[PDB]
Length: 42
Image (tube, rainbow, N blue to C red; front, top):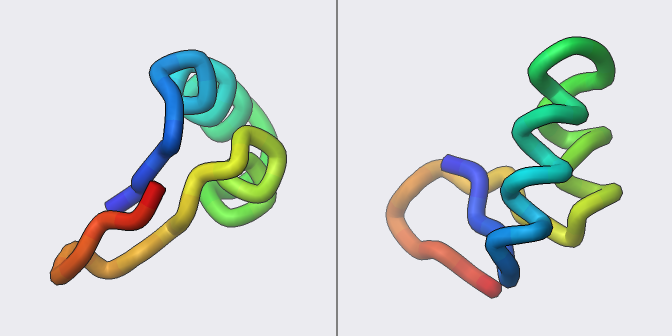
């Protein structure tokens, strides 16, 4: 699961990893955390 501290973060994240990059690389960008799914940080 990708946990983002903002909606803007998700928007940027999702589009970043939509075309290019990778989940983690894009999460790093937006401030989102690529987690498993047991918890969900902000």
